[PDB]
Amino acid sequence: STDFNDKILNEPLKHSDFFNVKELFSVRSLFDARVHLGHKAGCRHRFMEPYIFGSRLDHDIIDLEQTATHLQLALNFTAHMAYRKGIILFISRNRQFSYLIENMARDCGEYAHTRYFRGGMLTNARLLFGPTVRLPDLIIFLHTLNNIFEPHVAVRDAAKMNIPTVGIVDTNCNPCLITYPVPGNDDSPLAVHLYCRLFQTAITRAKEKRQQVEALYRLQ
Amino acid sequence: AGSRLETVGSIFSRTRDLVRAGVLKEKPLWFDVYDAFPPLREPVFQRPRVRYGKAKAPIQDIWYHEDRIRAKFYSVYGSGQRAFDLFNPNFKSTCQRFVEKYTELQKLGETDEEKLFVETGKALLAEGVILRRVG
Amino acid sequence: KNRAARVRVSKGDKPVTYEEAHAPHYIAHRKGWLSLHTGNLDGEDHAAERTVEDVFLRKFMWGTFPGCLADQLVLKRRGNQLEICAVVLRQLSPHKYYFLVGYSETLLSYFYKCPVRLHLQTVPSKVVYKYL
Amino acid sequence: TEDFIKKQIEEFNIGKRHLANMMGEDPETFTQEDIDRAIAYLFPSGLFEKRARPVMKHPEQIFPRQRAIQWGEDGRPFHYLFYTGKQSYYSLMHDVYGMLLNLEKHQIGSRWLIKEELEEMLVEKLSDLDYMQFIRLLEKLLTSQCGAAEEEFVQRFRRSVKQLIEPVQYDEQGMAFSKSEGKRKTAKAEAIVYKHGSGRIKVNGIDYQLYFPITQDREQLMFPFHFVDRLGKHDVTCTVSGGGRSAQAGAIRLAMAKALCSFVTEDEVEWMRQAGLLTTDPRVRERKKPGQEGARRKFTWKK
Amino acid sequence: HARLRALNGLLYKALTDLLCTPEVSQELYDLNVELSKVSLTPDFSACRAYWKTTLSAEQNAHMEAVLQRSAAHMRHLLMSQQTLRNVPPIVFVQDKGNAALAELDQLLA
RNA sequence: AGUAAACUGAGAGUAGAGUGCUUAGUUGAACAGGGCCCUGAAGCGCGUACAAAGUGUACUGAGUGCACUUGGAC
RNA sequence: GGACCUGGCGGUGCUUCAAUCCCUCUAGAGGAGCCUGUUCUGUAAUCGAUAAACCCCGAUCAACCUCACCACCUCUUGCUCAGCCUAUAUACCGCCAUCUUCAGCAAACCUGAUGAAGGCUACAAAGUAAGCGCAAGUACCCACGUAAAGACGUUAGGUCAAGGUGUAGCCC
Ligand SMILES: [Mg+2]
């Protein structure tokens, strides 16, 4: 079993992009999806200054170069977790995209929580679910702001429980605690659909590669 | 058993420190992936602070030399009727055509700004552009 | 407040059994009778003697099996026989159990002039029905 | 766990075979109802509560599903919406949302199931606001020109909201008649109404006016036949027993109305039922309560 | 108490003067509210201004709503005028005593 | 509301002993709409307190006069 | 001394309220007699109960007995490996009353830069809560109503005279 675990789990870590995620998107594709349209300068959150390319008529523009790098890293990490068969949970309280996110989660097999977030669903997970419950190994915040324009409590709870968080952070979000922030636009339907497709493809590719490598190992 | 002090260090920092301590029996699932591919910034907690003094937001506004031409064209002729088809990335409007013709006219050698503007208007009229005047 | 045959709530550390957890009003609805005889039936007699026998037998068994009975004692009066069914802990030695069983059988039988049988069911511990 | 449930399934099958052997019934054709009958006989219990009595059923019916752990051996929850905490409820909400989207793209008989009904259906614990949300979504689904393919699903949440015509028997002489019965307070009455008659109404072998010396009771007797305008068209024989005079009058009236139903048209029967002739009276004396003089008369409040 | 009676009289006069003009509000002025009396609670915790009601129910409701919305402004106006150094919260109460007399006279007619 | 009211039986207990108690049954209605002073329960809330206020200045015998502050309310 | 947090209080008004606070319907108590309980007087001569939550109450009940009272007389290891109806309910168990004609009580868990403290928003914003209780379930004749149930606490509430019992004291 030692040979199995090594050759399976540690092999992908050797290559920078084992899942070839970089081909899933291009700066041009992000620009078409409008990932780069932020909120007004007044709504800007201080910590998003490094990621904001500039202001155009008091409208922030997110540096798509930084977004491309961050998205590369985040998709790679998500694919790695999927390959390692961890539990991925998509969280977002944007009722406009709740249905899409739920369907994407069902399609990719990973789980989703778009509805109201009961207090302590992570901190008090053992009592709310059971002593043996397995907690999500990775979270993906399609929207990091709750419906009252405040950081989703899930972000802080995940930071507490030490569950890594990929997160689409808008120009008014607070990326301080998100492990893998992806500066971008969380409001454009095109941008959200692009994010959902990218994550679904990454998870599917990771799982299929996992199955293929497992079969390769077992046949020999 | 993982430390629940999210305001102290990062998840990676706390997990690594606890593992080194031996309190954590084994590294969690994601620790190896994080170590192999750390994010550009360590996710350390940090409280936002409101600028008070002469310190300013370093976000620079976006402008271009052609913004002058665009502003003047809007002032003289308004938005006209060629509504923006924002979906086509290669879309070019009447203002864009005026900007291009102004740029090539400047490149010709003509340098006076007002002469460039008026001659660009006349040249586009010759090209057939309906440069309707706003006022 | 009704103080009768009820276990008052506590911090939750007080284990209690089926009988102790059920209050009187539930009788004949959730819990049956710990003594089954025909004395109290309509038109019958000797209810007082059946009650006296029940009380004496219960006290006798409680004193005979100190810290051994893990549940109340169920009495059945078929014909003229008597059956005492008990739930006992598996703490006392089997030899002692058998000797006490035979002795009580014979003594009660001679005392009340009727055959008596004792049936013990053993458990590792008193059956907790909830904690109060 | 699932293995535990499978073991209980095997044990229950073996116990079923034991029971079939004990009762001599073919185990292959031995059914759940037969098991029920046999266990009832073999373990006579006198408890009023159907739940407090013994039971030997399939583990499926016996055990509570207890939400089935929700995570397999690996630990991955089965339901994609599992982490919500109300996975079935939110699955249903998502499904209704999808159906509403599909319908939007394309374009005194019942009610809704109560919140407890829905909770049992979803084996989940909901809230009042959750029930309101679900019901409002369902109502929108109705209003959205729900076709058969959608109305079929909706009826899964709908809940739907006539006097029996007794046979017309015949005497030895071939004269037709109808027999019926009715009880009021402590009185009981059996009334035979003949298809044709001259209005004679013999009670306990006695003429009605003689037996009921009170014009109020006479009016009670007359009420049904007057209502259907069949006075003097039926001969009636009423045997009453028990209770006081008014109770006897009510019982006879009820019995006569029921018997006359068989002879009056269905619309007439419905009219009588609406009036109240054919509705058994639930008003009965309320038992005296200890510590109070009457069913509600509290003893004179001392001071 | 004589002091309470004098306070009631002064407050009634002051409130009538206030309502005589659009000072509180043009909307309130247009309603032409008439005050039946003013009563101060024994502890000086409140001042009830009893205003005569009209026959129209919608008009009564609208007048009540406007009066409730303008009570605080009226209190401030009084305390600014110094008609009373301290004025408790003002509560507007509907008055319907005259309905009995009106309908009596209608029937008796 | 088969409620009140009225009436009539039965039972517990004793040797006996109630107009007491318990219980069964019979006939069997009237109002049900107003308000909150009185009781109590709430919310809106207010103000008490235990576990308008003040500074300066002057008269008078605690108030007043003038100015100032909110370390008060609107 | 400064700045804060919580509990208590009004002889605190406005608005909602309640066989249901007042009116509204019916039937009654008080006025007369008698039955009956209690208090004061009396008695050589009965204990307890004592505003709602005592007052045909402990008592489903006193001519002796009952009886624990008074008077008188009599007995001394005493029916009991004695006994005690003698104090202590302000030690308790046991059984109850009152709100309750309530619905809340709640352990165990999880923000204030980890202070006392706090934990609400459904187009939801940190609460979850086992368990107890209401509820639900059950008896009666329904699915109704009445019964039954009625948690934690409130009055040092009562009951040592149902019985048991800590404590006090008597044993010619
Ligand atoms: Mg945004």
Image: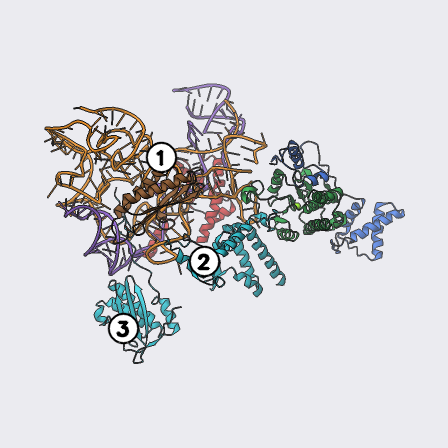
Chain colours: A green, B blue, C brown, D cyan, E red, F purple, G orange
Distance from the alpha carbon under mark 3 to that under mark 1: 86 Å
Q: Kindly state the secondary structure of the residue where label 3 is placed.
A: strand
Determine if marks 3 and 1 fall on one subunit.
no
* Residue depth check, mark 1 versus mark 2: number of the one nearer the observer: 2
**Of G107 and B81, which appears nearest the observer?**
G107
Is the residue at mark 2 in contact range of ligand 1, meaning its CB lies under 8 Å from it? no
Tell me residue D266's x, y (percent): 39, 73
Determine if marks 2 and 3 fall on one subunit.
yes
Q: Residue at x 46, y 53 (%)?
A: E58
Q: Is residue F21 left or right of residue F57?
A: left
Q: At label 2, which amino acid type do we have?
A: Leu
Would you say residue B49 is visible in this rendering?
Answer: no
CB within 8 Å, label 3 to label 1 = no
Would you say residue D134 is visible in this rendering?
Answer: yes
* Residue depth check, mark 3 versus mark 1: number of the one nearer the observer: 3
The number of callouts visible is 3
* Residue depth check, mark 2 versus mark 3: number of the one nearer the observer: 2
Give the label on residue D19, or none.
2
Q: Which residue is mark 1?
A: E2
- Quadrant where the C terminus of chain E sits is bottom left
Other residues around mark 3 within 10 Å, as few (<14) / some (14–19) / many (≥20): many
Q: At label 3, which amino acid type do we have?
A: Thr
Tell me residue D230's x, y (percent): 32, 75
Determine if marks 1 and 2 fall on one subunit.
no
What chain letter is assigned to the residue under label 3?
D
Distance from the alpha carbon under mark 2 to that under mark 3: 53 Å
